[PDB]
């Protein structure tokens, strides 16, 4: 009875819970303690769910149901209340603190006044009764909160101009987004909320230090914790305006840094010119000042000492005091090196590392000066070095320090950079400094180019930090247009900051040319400000940016870094390249970097280690097998060195802990000398590089390590706790776990490697073929980490290529310049804001999908050390330390070296996921999860026990799968596709057993029957899953192989293959021929669209499709056109009354927007406590989205199909992302069925292996000659019952039809012409035509039947032919076939060459003489001239044939035409003439120059309204010249194939169409009121009334292209080749 | 057609020119310690793989020129 | 009025500048017009039915590109800018480009330094013609490098010679010029050892 006790506990907790209220400047009492309420509700919901698990839940079910209901209401109310409260709080500070907004923007000021009045009314009401339910039971509280949020958002979005003026007031606000800038402005009074916004406004200021009153700014702080105390504190009381005291803080920060630098230099002058340095005093001086200040003081002291020494030996013959400078530098370096060999606080350790690097550079420079025998201070060997000159006598503190290199002179900007990672001053970096300073002095830009990872952006940032400047890194892309770059340049000009635009060549060429103007103007302004004649009193040079006058600060510069030759990069126009001084960065000095880094981290043998590690990296690059994900550049070495330092620190700590726990004896020197540094480096190298290596490269790399590092071995640690958590997680998820060499050792080893890489890098790439366990690996790791460390882990799975890049990262409106968040940007911003405590959780953003440079290069800054997501609007989002970016890809064939080097790699081979593990997972899931939602469990466990011997290593299934890989399949064979098909079929077998038990309540199935049935069905399922996507020969081959290896009794039949047999529920083989009866179709149902003649292939595929669809498993039918894929699927769906099929017709231009329109029409989004769920409008019905050309959509240059990726996301993950609000939408009661031609057919692309993993493929080939004979003999026998005298001729007639069709298919193939496709569709049309001709006639001799047969053959097989010889061949072959199969008939009467049939001269479709038809056409042409169109026509035989063909097509339902011929041949005129005869109203779209897609949509809406609502027959004549965009062809494709465009009618246009359709149905006398039935009636009317006549020129490549962009033009449209006049 | 016969003759001559066999290098415990073998195995591996691919493609081209097999997308592209 | 073509605001500025200059007689230059061929055709059609001022001139600087419309090429006069045919032509072009007053400054050694720089530039650019032997790739050794080298020579000669009419050839900062034009001016584009 613990359920009732905990329910009472929750009741008491909620009745006692009250809303914590705190005042706001004596205005309102805000809700406080959001996190407590949130996790209380979460824990209560979880408790109620765990109670629902219990069986005693039933007695308290209704109560607990209402409890979950009210808990969900509390969640919904407060999921918006917190946002509303924050929005009102920072909106109040804008509409109250600022007085200019009243005059500038009065209307929304009054709107906000009204909304604030409403909010304070509700808030006072809350204050009266702070009880949680008393807040909840308020009438319309949820709706009131929603409307308040909507109105506040509307007000917020209309404050852009005020923000632009505010940014103009304080220049640094330009790098702050709209949301954050409103946050800053509104919360100026509450400074505690501005602490998290300083990092985007300053280089190293992450927070400010305030007194107890929060009114005086005492100083600033960095992210590490280093503090700078202002000499003159800034008081916010005297300067209430946010911008004023922010500017005062900036100026004070500069001045106090200058004064502290002066003091530090004065103090460090003692350490200089001193023979011996006391370590204690030097450490005290280091701890006293900031890192940048101590580095600057050391540089200034060294520069002054070297200058003094050089001046001393200016006479040449004097002594050499430069040796004294070198000795002092060496003594200081030794003191520093001894300091890092022992334990230090992290801040002092970083300071010592920076000082060691700087002093190593000084020692190198001094040695170079001594070696070159330099004796003059004006020698270029000294002028080329970066010299620092300090002038304490200068009154202005900011100009006391001057930094010079060659002829260039700069002033230290004194911007607090915090503690930045200094780079080793390699000779390449020295060259970069020289070139960049020379460019800056000439007032040009910097363009360091080269391959990825050669220290270009870092070199620019290090140079900027060296001069004390603010360096901004902008990850440029193609949406950095002219306006966004103009705004960024304005911000840089006003602030006075450096802009490092890395990936500059990712812009469009036109955009680069446009930006060249702004660059040139800024450079000219800088050049004019450089001239000494300019004075402070004279107004600062004003450059014109974006039609505005913007002040230009001297400190600014424009650096662009680019990788030449990489994919997805443009070229820079010569007018832009001449503005930048380029530098080639190709070969960084890796050895020097490694040596200095190892020296600074405390390694005693740094030189040897570097000399052993750098050639090791070259050996790895040149010796391991080449792979696309392999990277061994400078970034890899940097990661290795950092990991080595961390490992050394952890080993020192472990040794110290062992020493304190075992006795008391600790000596820093003893530990330092007795430390295996080689082992540490090997451990770091293995932890960083082994995961990315392929199976065959691991022993090669280990032998390489043994060769370069002999005697040292790697012993990977045993994460016993993590291994236990992984074991538990695998047990709860039915996964196979193994330690070492057991089944699953490789997979868990990969998981541990993934954990180790996550600990090091913030960007990962799980690269490996489909079905290698990547998703399971990272999911299991996430759950294990959550259950071990206690930090909740959440994951955001994003399919990057299933959505457009604008939807993925965001878009900037070219008109209003407003930023709309994308998907990844929205997720990252939500995590950064942490409004619901997302910063305390482990956030992993997994980019499950294909990777190409178009979308992944925008993440270069995120994956870099910058950890910034730079947006085109100047915003930058800092990556939180708890966020990991993960890429789950199958190959890296298209990503450049920039992306590969930026992410740690874990390579998953297909041997990681052994087949035994998949078998064990399937068996565990079979034995645990019920199939219905228990007899189900008992049947499931019994069946799993029966299948256990076969689902083993070297079993029947494994051997069959190995052999099936050697056959030939229509689609590429993957292991997981076959395994999924087999598992689904076995589940269906279990459901069949359960259904048999249900139908026999008295006598349930015994053990022996179950064994027999399960074994036979297992063999059947293996045969139909491992060879379902292959021809009949391969099916027979696999059957024979199974008959050999398998031991289970198989059909004893001699020649009949096993695949011809099903497994009856009684547990015995029964041939499929027992289910193929010789049916007799009704006369009126001859060749009807829904009539299927049962054959062996038909019943086999029907059973297979029913088995797969009963599981709601997505499936794809692949086969040649007209084979019967759609017919078989519809036949299988007729046996499932709870499935509604919706037809989709993919084209070359198909995008996920088509699927979205179908979802909008047939489904509805509903908000649920678990999220948005998309379900069909009809209740209890499953929507089957039938995609007819799934492999047709265009494949980009990077080998992807966007709609295919969308379908893969919606199948594997069970949902997609709503790009309107970035909300995850979970599919419900929706399944997908695909149809496609073989990928070898032209215009078809092979589906991705990740997509084929989930979808079984069944190969529906052409019916054989025997099958065709059966089907069409049945059809003819049913048809020929009209004339009893003709009944005896059905058998020869069907034989003649089959023979001619077979000859026609062989003779004309797709190699000759794209439209030369023949299928049983032609036979069905043949039978339909013969039946329609014979239907009204009462009697008819055999000669008339042969004449009708020949005429139909001519109309089907000769109308589409191009050349004359092909038509002659068709005529001769018709004659020969008819004479062969119908001897003793009079040829002349039945086969007179002018075969013409028309119903114009009689009520029936009878043969017509040429001359009488010509006279009738002349009379009708005279009437047509007098009535419709007075354009005289000359009549000839071909015109008569063409008008007869058009009349034939126009009388058919859904009869569409494709008239191909040279222009001016009369196609349009003949179409109009025939349509006027048949009563059709001719409709043509008046295309002009301004005709766009919307006008075409309006014309289509008008034509559909007329053809479906008014029951008006319309002949929609459309020319190929009327096609202006691909949307025209897409909508035409949909309309031709289905008869209705799904997204054409929406909003108001939909309701008007509904009303008109209701009126039309009333006119016809039908009783329809629902929108679904009315729309179905409208579609039927459009099908019955609308005919589309498409005319085009006989282009060669044009026809091939149209066979792909509009496939329905060749499947639903009858092709007539008018051609040129013969 | 003329181009079919010309390509048939060219492909037949190419098959005559290109050799047919290439055996991979065997791994051994002491062989891995030899960097010569470490490179040399990669060489024979790439050589054998590319030789097999080229021979298969040219055999398919010859087969098409004789009309025994149908043209696919990749096969058509290779012919082009 | 020089306008960089490629943006819609650029098109509007070009239209306004042409409309103003056809009446005021000022010059208008548009850079990189090969990026907008359709707007190029529209501009040609606009130009054909126009009667501009006597002193109006319109320069359309572009790269040799097949996308440029034929009618515009037939309408205008084509000038091709490209490497000079030889060393002599290269030196003549370099000496013509540099203003006379710049070379004839106070130090009499400035003229010889400029002549040496011009000969070096001609030698470097002519080796570009023989791509595999003269260099390793088609480097972009252009007029910008020449201007930067001339500016460096001027700066260091003025630094060393404090306005003196003559400076000893020993005192000329050879090391400065050599190191700078080897590491930053000409050596910046060099990516091969
Ligand atoms: N450790 C394991 N033991 C047993 N079965 C496993 C294990 N890991 C994965 N599987 C199973 O094998 C298959 C692999 O699925 P998973 O999603 O992990 O593949 P993947 O390599 O990420 O594929 P893709 O490239 O298509 O995303 C699934 O059917 C899963 O249930
Ligand atoms: N002199 C150096 N000392 C230390 N690390 C360096 C040095 N030069 C480059 N690096 C490292 O090499 C990588 C280069 O980064 P970055 O310059 O941004 O790349 P890219 O050259 O592709 O723009 C970074 O990890 C950086 O810290
Ligand atoms: N067993 C059968 N009984 C009756 N008609 C068949 C049979 N098999 C094939 N057909 C004919 O073949 C045609 C198949 O066309 P369709 O279903 O559109 O194939 P796809 O969708 O693959 O192009 C149908 O028109 C049908 O009349
Ligand atoms: N049989 C014919 N006798 C005389 N003129 C004809 C005949 N057929 C077409 N034309 C001429 O063709 C013109 C119409 O061409 P049209 O049918 O619009 O070309 P298209 O078929 O390319 O649309 C008419 O002006 C008519 O004079
Ligand atoms: Mg996966």
Image (cartoon, helix red, strand yellow):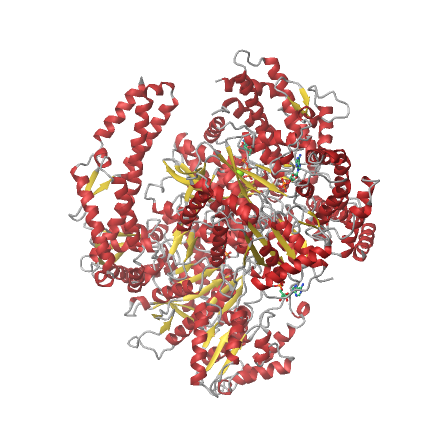
Relative to residue A1365, is residue A750 drawn left or right? Answer: left
Q: Is residue A1282 visible?
A: yes
Question: Eyeballing the image, is A1511 above or below A1061?
Answer: below
The image quadrant that residue C181 belongs to is bottom right
Residue A816 point in image, percent of width and height: 37, 61
Q: Is residue A604 visible?
A: no
Question: Eyeballing the image, is A1080 above or below A1515?
Answer: above
Residue A432 point in image, percent of width and height: 49, 64
- Between A35 and A1190, the one lying in front of the other is A1190
Question: Eyeballing the image, is A125 above or below A488?
Answer: above
Residue A1045 point in image, percent of width and height: 72, 24
Residue A1270 point in image, percent of width and height: 72, 33
Quarter of the N terminus of chain A within the rendering: top left
Residue at image location 64% in from the left, 72% down from the top: C128
The image quadrant that residue A1266 belongs to is top right
Quarter of the C terminus of chain A within the rendering: bottom right
Residue at image location 42% in from the left, 64% down from the top: A485
Residue at image location 43% in from the left, 78% down from the top: C17
Relative to residue A933, is residue A80 drawn left or right? Answer: left
Q: Which quarter holds ligand 3? A: top right
Q: Residue furthest top?
A: A1002
- Give the tally of numbered discs: 0
Relative to residue C17, is residue A198 drawn left or right? Answer: left
Relative to residue A163, is residue A1161 drawn left or right? Answer: right
- Between A39 and A258, the one lying in front of the other is A39
């Amino acid at each position: 009875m613990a359920l009732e006790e905990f329910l009472k506990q929750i009741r008491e907790v909620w009745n006692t819970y009250e809303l914590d209220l705190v005042n706001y400047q004596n205005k309102c009492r805000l809700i406080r303690g959001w996190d407590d309420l949130f996790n209380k509700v979460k824990e209560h919901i979880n408790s109620v769910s765990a109670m629902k698990l219990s069986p005693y839940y039933k007695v308290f079910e209704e109560d607990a149901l209402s409890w979950e209901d009210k808990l969900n209401r509390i969640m919904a109310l407060f999921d918006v209340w917190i946002d509303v409260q924050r929005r009102w709080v920072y909106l109040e500070g804008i509409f109250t603190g600022s007085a200019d907004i009243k005059h500038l923007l009065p209307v929304e000021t009054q709107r906000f006044q009204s909304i604030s009045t409403e909010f304070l009314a509700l808030m006072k009401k809350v204050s009266k009764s702070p009880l949680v339910m008393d807040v909840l039971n308020i009438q319309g509280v949820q709706r009131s909160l929603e409307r308040l949020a909507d109105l506040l958002g509307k007000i917020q979005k209309a404050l852009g101009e005020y923000l632009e003026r505010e940014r103009s007031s304080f220049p640094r606000f330009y790098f702050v987004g709209d949301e954050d800038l409103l946050e800053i402005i509104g919360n100026s009074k509450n400074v505690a909320k501005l602490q998290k916004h300083f990092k985007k406004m300053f280089a190293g200021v992450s927070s400010i230090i305030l007194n107890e009153d929060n009114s005086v700014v005492l100083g600033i702080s960095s992210r590490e914790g280093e503090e700078v105390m202002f000499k003159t504190p800034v008081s916010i009381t005297e300067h209430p305006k946010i911008n004023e005291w922010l500017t005062l803080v900036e100026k004070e920060m500069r001045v106090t840094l200058a004064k502290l630098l002066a003091e530090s230099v004065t103090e460090v002058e003692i350490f200089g010119k001193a023979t011996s340095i006391d370590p204690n005093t030097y450490i005290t001086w280091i701890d006293k000042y900031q890192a940048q200040l101590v580095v600057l003081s050391a540089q200034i002291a060294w520069s002054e000492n070297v200058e003094t020494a050089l001046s001393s030996m200016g006479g040449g013959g004097d002594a050499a005091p430069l040796h004294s400078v070198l000795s002092n530098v060496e003594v200081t370096l030794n003191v520093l090196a001894d300091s890092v060999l022992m334990e230090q606080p992290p801040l002092r350790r970083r300071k010592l590392e920076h000082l060691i690097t700087e002093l190593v550079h000084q020692r190198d420079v001094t040695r170079s000066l001594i070696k070159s025998k330099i004796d003059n201070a004006k020698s270029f060997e000294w002028l080329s070095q970066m010299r620092f000159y300090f002038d304490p006598k200068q009154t202005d503190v900011l100009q006391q320090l001057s930094i010079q290199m060659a002829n260039a002179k700069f002033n230290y900007g004194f911007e607090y950079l915090g503690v930045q990672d200094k780079l080793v001053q390699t000779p390449l970096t020295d060259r970069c400094y020289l070139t960049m300073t020379q460019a800056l002095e000439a007032r040009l830009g910097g363009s360091p180019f080269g391959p990825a990872g050669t220290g270009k952006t870092e070199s620019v940032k290090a140079l900027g930090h060296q001069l004390g400047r603010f360096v901004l890194v902008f990850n440029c892309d193609e949406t950095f247009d002219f306006q966004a770059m103009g705004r960024i340049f304005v911000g840089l000009c006003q602030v006075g900051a450096w802009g490092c635009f890395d990936e500059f060549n990712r812009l469009e060429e036109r955009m680069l040319s446009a930006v060249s103007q702004q660059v040139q103007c800024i450079q000219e302004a800088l050049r004019e400000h450089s001239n000494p004649n300019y004075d402070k009193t004279s107004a600062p040079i004003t450059c014109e940016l974006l039609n505005k006058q913007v002040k230009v600060s001297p400190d600014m510069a424009i650096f662009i870094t680019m990788n030449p030759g990489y994919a997805g990069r443009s070229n820079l126009p010569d007018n832009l390249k001449k503005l930048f001084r380029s530098l080639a960065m190709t070969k960084p000095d890796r050895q020097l970097i490694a040596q200095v880094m190892l020296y600074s981290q405390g390694f005693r043998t740094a030189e040897v280690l570097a000399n052993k590690i750098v050639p090791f990296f070259k050996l790895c690059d040149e010796q391991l097998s080449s792979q696309s994900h392999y990277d061994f550049g400078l970034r890899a070495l940097k990661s290795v060195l950092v990991s080595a330092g961390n490992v050394k620190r952890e080993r020192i700590q472990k040794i110290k802990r062992e020493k304190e726990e075992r006795g008391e004896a600790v000596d820093e020197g003893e530990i330092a000398e007795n430390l295996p540094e080689q082992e540490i480096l090997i451990q770091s190298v293995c932890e960083t590089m082994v995961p990315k290596l392929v199976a065959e490269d691991i022993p090669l790399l280990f032998s390489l390590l043994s060769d370069v590092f002999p005697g040292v071995q790697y012993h990977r640690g045993e994460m016993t706790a993590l291994r236990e958590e992984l074991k538990k997680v695998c047990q709860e998820m039915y996964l196979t776990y193994g330690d070492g060499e057991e089944v699953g050792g490789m997979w868990v080893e990969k998981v541990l490697q993934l954990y180790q890489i996550t600990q090091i890098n913030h960007g990962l790439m799980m690269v490996g073929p489909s079905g290698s366990g990547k998703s399971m690996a990272w999911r299991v790791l996430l759950k294990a980490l959550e259950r071990l460390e206690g930090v909740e882990g959440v994951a955001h799975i994003i399919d990057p290529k299933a959505i457009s890049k604008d939807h993925l990262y965001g878009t900037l409106d070219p008109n209003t310049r407003e930023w709309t968040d994308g998907l990844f940007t929205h997720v990252l911003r939500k995590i950064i804001d942490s409004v619901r405590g997302e910063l305390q959780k482990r956030q992993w953003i997994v980019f499950d999908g294909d990777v190409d440079p178009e979308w992944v290069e925008n993440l270069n800054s995120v994956l870099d050390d910058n950890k910034l997501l730079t947006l085109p609007n100047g915003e930058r989002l800092s990556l939180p330390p708890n966020v990991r970016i993960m890429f789950e890809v199958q190959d890296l064939k298209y990503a450049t070296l920039a992306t590969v080097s930026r992410c740690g790699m874990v390579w998953f081979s297909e041997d990681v996921l052994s087949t035994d593990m998949i078998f064990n997972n399937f068996l565990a899931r079979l034995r645990s999860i019920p199939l219905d939602e228990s007899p189900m469990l008992q049947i499931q466990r019994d069946a799993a026990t029966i299948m256990q011997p076969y689902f083993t290593s070297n079993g029947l299934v494994t051997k069959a799968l190995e052999h099936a890989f050697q056959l030939e399949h229509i689609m590429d064979l993957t292991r997981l596709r076959c395994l999924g098909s087999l598992f689904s079929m076995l589940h269906q077998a279990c459901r069949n057993v359960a259904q048999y038990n249900a139908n026999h309540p008295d006598f349930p199935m015994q053990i022996e029957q179950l064994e027999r049935y399960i074994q036979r069905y297992l063999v059947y399922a293996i045969l139909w899953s491992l060879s379902g996507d292959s021809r009949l020969k391969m099916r027979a081959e696999l059957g024979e192989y199974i008959r050999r290896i398998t031991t289970v009794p198989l059909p004893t039949a001699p020649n009949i293959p096993i695949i011809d047999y099903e497994v009856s529920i009684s547990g015995e083989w029964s041939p499929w021929q027992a289910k193929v009866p010789q049916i007799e179709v009704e006369t009126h149902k001859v060749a009807a669209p829904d009539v299927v003649v049962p054959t062996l292939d038909t019943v086999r595929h029907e059973a297979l499709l029913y088995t797969w669809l009963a599981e709601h498993k997505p499936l794809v039918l692949c086969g040649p056109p007209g084979s019967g894929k759609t017919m078989t699927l519809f036949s299988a769906l007729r046996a499932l009354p709870d499935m509604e099929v919706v037809g989709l017709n993919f084209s070359s231009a198909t995008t996920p927007e088509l699927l979205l329109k179908t979802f909008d029409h047939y489904c509805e989004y509903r908000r649920t406590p678990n999220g948005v769920v998309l379900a069909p409008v009809q209740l209890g019905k499953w929507l089957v989205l039938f995609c007819d050309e799934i492999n047709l959509p265009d494949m980009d240059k990077y080998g992807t199909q966007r709609v295919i990726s969308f379908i893969r996301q919606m199948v594997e993950h069970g949902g997609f992302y709503r790009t309107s609000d970035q909300t995850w939408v979970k599919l419900e009661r929706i399944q997908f069925v695909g149809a496609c031609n073989p990928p070898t057919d032209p215009g078809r692309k092979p589906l991705s292996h990740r997509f084929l993993r989930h979808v079984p493929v069944v190969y529906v080939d052409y019916p054989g000659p025997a099958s065709l004979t059966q089907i069409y003999g049945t059809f003819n026998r049913a048809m020929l019952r009209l004339i009893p005298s003709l009944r005896t001729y059905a058998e020869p007639l069907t034989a003649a039809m089959v023979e001619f069709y077979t000859m026609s298919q062989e003779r004309f193939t797709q190699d000759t012409q794209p439209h030369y496709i023949y299928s049983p569709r032609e036979m069905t049309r043949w039978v339909r035509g013969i039946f329609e001709a014979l239907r009204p006639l009462e009697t008819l001799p055999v000669e008339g039947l042969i004449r009708i047969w020949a005429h139909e053959a001519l109309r089907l097989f000769q109308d589409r032919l191009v050349e004359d010889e092909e038509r002659r061949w068709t005529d001769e072959n018709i004659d020969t076939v008819a004479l062969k199969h119908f001897p003793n008939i009079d040829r002349e009467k039945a086969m007179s060459r002018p075969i013409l049939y028309s119903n114009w001269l009689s009520k029936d479709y009878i043969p017509v003489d040429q001359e009488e038809l010509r006279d009738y056409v002349k009379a009708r042409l005279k009437v047509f001239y007098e009535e419709e169109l007075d354009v005289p026509l000359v009549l000839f035989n071909e015109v008569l044939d063409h008008v007869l063909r058009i009349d034939r097509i126009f009388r058919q339902p859904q009869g569409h035409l494709l008239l191909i011929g040279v222009s001016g041949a009369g196609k349009t005129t003949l179409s109009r003439f025939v349509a006027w005869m048949n009563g059709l109203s001719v409709y043509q779209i008046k295309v002009h120059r301004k005709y766009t897609g919307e006008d075409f949509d309006e014309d289509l809406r008008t034509v559909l309204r007329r053809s479906g609502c008014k029951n008006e027959k319309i002949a929609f004549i459309m020319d190929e010249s009327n096609v202006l965009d691909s949307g025209f062809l897409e909508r035409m494709n949909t309309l031709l194939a289905n008869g209705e465009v799904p997204g054409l009618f929406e909003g108001d246009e939909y309701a008007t169409l509904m009303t008109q359709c209701k009126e039309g149905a009333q006119k016809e006398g039908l009783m329809l009121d629902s929108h679904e039935e009315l729309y179905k009636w409208f579609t039927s009317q459009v099908i019955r009334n609308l005919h589309v006549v498409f005319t085009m020129n006989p282009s060669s490549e044009g026809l091939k292209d149209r066979a792909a962009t509009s496939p329905a033009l060749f499947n639903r449209c009858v092709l007539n080749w008018f051609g040129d006049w013969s | 057609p003329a181009w079919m016969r010309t390509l048939h003759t060219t492909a037949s001559n190419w098959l005559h020119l290109i050799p047919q066999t290439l055996s991979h290098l065997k791994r051994t415990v002491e062989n891995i310690k030899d960097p010569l073998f470490r490179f040399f195995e990669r060489e024979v591996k790439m050589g054998a793989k590319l030789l097999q691919d080229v021979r298969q493609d040219l055999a398919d081209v010859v087969q098409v020129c004789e009309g025994k097999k149908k043209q696919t997308n990749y096969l058509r592209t290779l012919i082009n | 009025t020089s306008i960089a073509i490629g943006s819609a605001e650029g098109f509007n500025q070009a239209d306004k500048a042409i409309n103003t200059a056809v009446k005021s007689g000022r010059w208008v230059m548009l850079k990189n017009v090969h990026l907008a061929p359709g707007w190029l055709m529209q501009l040609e059609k606009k130009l054909h039915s126009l009667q501009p001022h006597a002193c109006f001139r319109l320069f359309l600087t572009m790269e040799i590109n097949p996308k440029v419309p034929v009618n515009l090429l037939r309408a205008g006069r084509i000038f091709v800018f490209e490497p000079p045919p030889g060393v002599k032509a290269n030196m003549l072009r370099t000496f013509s480009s540099i203003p006379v007053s710049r070379i004839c400054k106070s130090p009499n050694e400035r003229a010889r330094l400029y002549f040496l720089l011009a000969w070096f530039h001609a030698i470097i650019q002519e080796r570009l013609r023989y791509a595999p032997l003269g260099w390793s790739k088609k480097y972009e050794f252009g007029e910008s490098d020449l201007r930067s080298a001339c500016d460096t020579v001027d700066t260091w000669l003025d630094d060393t010679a404090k306005g003196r009419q003559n400076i000893s050839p020993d005192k000329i900062p050879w090391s400065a010029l050599k190191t700078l034009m080897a590491q930053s001016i000409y050596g910046g584009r060099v990516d091969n050892e």
